[PDB]
Image (cartoon, coloured by chain):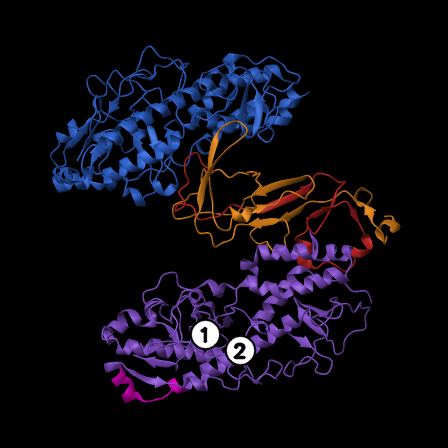
Chain colours: A blue, B orange, C red, D purple
């Protein structure tokens, strides 16, 4: 059976799925399950099942298949062509698991205190709960040197549901008692450039993407409130007037602005949507151009594997190179989720003032 | 056009009568249940919506909400058919719901219980 | 559809069926009347038995 | 002249017109005037004029018809099949006339311009408005055994405009002076089941519909609000805190919940549409499933007298019996108007505190 190439928006959707952590990969051994990484055989993009050895479209989501369909194949695409996409999606999933565990820790420690002392600390405005960062995800791939990106994924069901519940609970307890955790941050564009760093923090560098050649093993980069506690310019009522997130982010139950965090795990911040959006999904803070840069190597293998007429008729005007350039121009809009641009224009308590340290995440009045 | 076929007083088989057809366009909400014989609706008196999970052909779960007024198309007693849904020019915007980034899809249910008793 | 729970308080629409729906037949050998498949048809009895309400809502 | 059956929705429209009280009926000796009862020849349903001897569409609303058009008829449809529909229409017309006369007489009693007595009632309350329950439409068949439904109707011009004017004026005055009339029931589904009854009214049982089998002749049911004035707990302040109708139905200037009535005639409440719907309309409280039952003998007779192919091509899938079952499956939607479900969701005074008995309609304060 003869096959054909997929259209451009399908490739864009494949990249979006990969950087959302949800590319469904079928291998001969484990099937559609991705619990232990295997050699990919097909992937799903734009409602089409594309084989990874010829990139020809075979099957769709409408009809269920359990084996790779019989067809005529090129066998010219290799593993190095899409290994970067595979790495991106797998590490995206790993980071989601790590952040899930960390948020669970934060919420369970929040529940350990009573509301009465919570309001009394709101009057006080000091720290209340502190969690050692050496227990923060001891067996992750960012935290442990003995791990790698080929480890099996932690068995989690309805990860996003738990994320939503714990996130809304933690932020509601924050806005109840004027509290401030150190790890919360107003805008990650400033985290990438414009922030001061501590003596042990200046060694850190940001890759601004999920790159295989980079080093993702590092510590926790919190926004150390030692420097703000060093700033008595705010009285207690004024510490409520400035340090409370609702002074910049707004009241959480009635706002449409996102919240961001410092690079807690893997030197990659996490962005959460507003409540009135509909659900508090988690996204990475990665530019769409860096997203498109993963599949650069695949274009050459495609142009060397297939005839030029098929590429011209399937991909569009100008072929694969033309689609690549047009989508690079259209990167800011197609590859960026709507929650990344939605941030507070004005923040009276800008995060730029004070340095960040590697150490103990804490919650403060 | 054979005049004996179009003016026969006796039954004629479907293939002998058929001709290559043309597409049609509808809008379900504007349609009525009494006139359209291929629609089903949960009675509006329910007022207790419920959330259900369904898996696809690959093995990724999804979440859904059903309530009073949810309309379905009764597939049986119809030849093979092709459906295309076009949602252009609509908002679907609520106080706590933003249509940006949301996923809309078809689902097929196969059950013995009639739809309204759900 | 979502990857998490959809709070019923959040969404009040019953469906997304308020849009345009294009139907195109996929078999030119079967015939329906008033929405149900029939194996044989009698053309003389179709004369003068349809109203516009029953015609615009036909398959 | 060959003729064909009417479609199902025209039949549903016929049933709805019959239970609203207006169906245009053509008789040979009468024409298109339905004041004096006669045997119907033609009826209009859904813009289709149909003969009742063959039940075949013989004309439309566009062209003027003066006699019965000459056509080929099978004459196998008798009169006893649709005598039920004709009976329902005529009884609903009689009952509408009765309710209009009652409302007009009650307003004319309440129209009294006694300003000094009015502000003394405002000062104290009490009951000064009273009408004898033996004067509520004595000439009607509902109060007199002798009168029959074949008697000529009450010749009335513009019943709906007069009824709207009288109802609106009465409600305006009652809400203006904070009076306490004895006509309303917040929930009418309580009347047939769950309401306390007076000593005389314990024996009576309600047929919940209009038909020849049941009894349609009885007295007036009203709330016992005399004991309310005899109850020392009630006070003008308390009567304006809980008992006043505006506490529950909403202010008639801006109310959007429809107003009901007690079983004044025929053991059937009459629902009055709210003003925000654009007009005031009076409907009986028959349930749609009961409304559907009136054409069962008609369905059987059609299945006896007409051919299979014509019935299948006209009524639709499953034949006429299939149409009957399908309309029974969805009766609450198509066979019940919206004004019959616009009753207020929550109430303050309630519907169940004082037993309903055979008494004079009275207004207190």
Query: Left or right of D299: which side holds D307?
Result: right
Residue in the image at 28% along x and 88% along y: D117
Numbered disc in front, either 2 or 1: 1
In front of the other: D303 or B23: D303
Q: Examine the image and state in which quarter residue B81 appears.
A: top right
Report the residue at 46% width, 17% height from top. Answer: A84
Reply above or below: D124 against D254.
below
* B67 lies above or below D358: above
Q: How far from the left and from the top, in percent, is residue B25?
A: 64, 48
Instruction: Write down the residue under mark 2.
Output: D95
Q: Which mark is residue B11?
A: none
In the rendered structure, the answer to whether residue D126 lies left or right of residue C48 reads: left
Q: Name the residue tied to disc 1.
A: D263
Q: Is residue A24 left or right of residue D39?
A: left
Q: Is residue D3 magenta?
A: no
- Chain at tag 1: D
Measured Cα–Cα span from mark 2 to mark 1: 11 Å
Image quarter of residue A48? top right
Q: Position of residue B24 (x, y in %)?
A: 67, 47
> Residue D6, can we see it?
no
Q: For numbered disc 2, what is the local secondary structure?
A: helix
Is residue D117 highlighted in magenta? Answer: yes
Q: Position of residue B107 (x, y in %)?
A: 55, 38
> What span is colored magenta in the figure?
D109-121
Can residue D89 be seen here? The reply is yes
Residue D161 drawn above or below residue A311: below
Looking at the rendered structure, the secondary structure element under dot 1 is loop
User: Mark 2 belongs to which subunit?
Assistant: D
Going from N to C along the chain, the mark reached first, 2 or 1, is 2
């Amino acid at each position: 059976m003869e096959v054909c190439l997929p259209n451009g928006h399908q490739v864009v959707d494949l990249i979006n799925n990969a950087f959302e952590g949800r590319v469904s990969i079928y291998s001969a051994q484990e099937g559609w399950d991705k619990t232990i990484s295997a050699q990919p055989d097909m992937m799903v993009c734009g409602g089409a099942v594309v084989c990874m050895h010829c990139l020809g479209v075979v099957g769709s989501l409408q009809r269920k298949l359990k084996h790779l369909p019989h067809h005529r194949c090129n066998q010219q695409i290799r593993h190095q062509d899409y290994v970067d996409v595979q790495f991106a999606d797998r590490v995206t999933a790993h980071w989601k698991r790590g952040m899930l565990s960390f948020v669970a820790q934060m919420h369970e420690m929040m529940n350990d205190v009573s509301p009465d002392d919570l309001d009394r600390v709101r009057t006080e405005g000091g720290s209340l709960v502190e969690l050692n960062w050496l227990q923060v995800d001891p067996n992750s791939m960012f935290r442990s040197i003995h791990s790698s990106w080929t480890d099996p994924l932690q068995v989690v069901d309805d990860l996003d549901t738990k994320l939503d519940q714990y996130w809304t609970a933690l932020n509601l307890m924050i806005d109840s008692s004027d509290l401030i955790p150190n790890f919360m941050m107003r805008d990650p564009s400033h985290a990438f450039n414009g922030v001061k760093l501590g003596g042990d923090a200046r060694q850190t560098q940001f890759s601004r993407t999920f790159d295989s050649r980079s080093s993702l093993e590092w510590g926790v980069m919190v926004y150390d409130y030692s420097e703000l506690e060093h700033d008595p310019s705010k009285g207690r009522a004024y510490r409520k007037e400035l340090v409370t997130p609702a002074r910049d982010f707004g009241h959480f139950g009635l706002s449409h602005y996102s919240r961001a965090t410092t690079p807690i795990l893997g030197k990659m911040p996490a962005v959460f949507s507003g409540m009135l959006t509909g659900n508090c999904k988690m996204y990475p803070f990665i530019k769409g151009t860096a997203k498109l840069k993963t599949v650069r190597k695949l274009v050459e293998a495609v142009n060397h594997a297939w005839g030029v007429e098929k590429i011209r008729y399937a991909l569009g005007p100008g072929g694969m190179t033309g689609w690549y350039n047009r989508t690079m121009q259209q990167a800011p809009i197609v590859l960026t989720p709507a929650a990344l641009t939605m941030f507070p224009d004005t923040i009276k308590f800008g995060d730029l003032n004070y340095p960040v340290m590697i150490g103990d995440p804490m919650i403060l009045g | 056009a054979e005049p004996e076929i179009i003016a026969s007083l006796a039954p004629v088989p479907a293939p002998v009568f058929a001709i290559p057809p043309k597409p049609a366009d509808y809008n379900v909400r504007t349609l009525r249940i009494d006139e359209a014989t291929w629609l089903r609706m949960i009675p509006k008196s329910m007022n207790t919506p419920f959330q259900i999970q369904v898996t696809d052909n690959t093995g990724t779960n999804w979440h859904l909400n059903l309530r009073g007024g949810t309309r379905v198309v009764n597939l049986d007693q119809i030849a093979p058919m092709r459906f295309v849904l076009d949602l252009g020019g609509k908002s679907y915007k609520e106080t706590s719901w933003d249509p940006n980034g949301k996923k809309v899809g078809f689902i097929v249910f196969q059950s013995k219980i009639p739809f309204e008793l759900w | 559809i979502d990857s998490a729970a959809i709070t019923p308080t959040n969404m009040t629409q019953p469906d997304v069926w308020d849009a345009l729906l294009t139907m195109s037949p996929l078999s030119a050998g079967e015939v329906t009347v008033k929405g149900a498949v029939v194996s044989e048809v009698v053309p003389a009895d179709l004369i003068g038995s349809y109203t516009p309400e029953s015609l615009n809502a036909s398959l």
